[PDB]
Image (cartoon, rainbow over all chains, first blue to last red; front, side, top):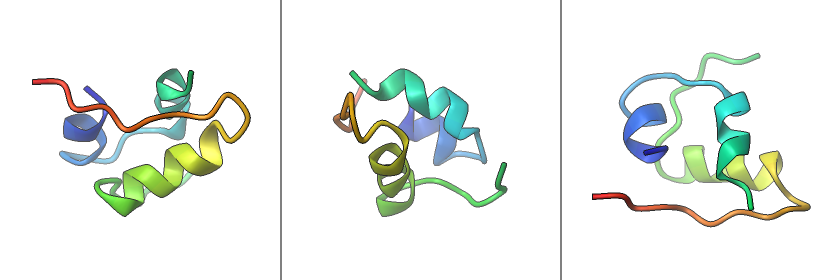
Length: 21
Length: 30
């Protein structure tokens, strides 16, 4: 998902926007 | 534009400053 991906390595806040609403 | 690891409050504080308007809710997919 989003935690196992940015918490497993460094992702981008751009993909963090796909977890808004 | 950063290179910091995102996990608990780190990945969370991010969404908070990412959506703000639309909002957001931590997700826990199996």
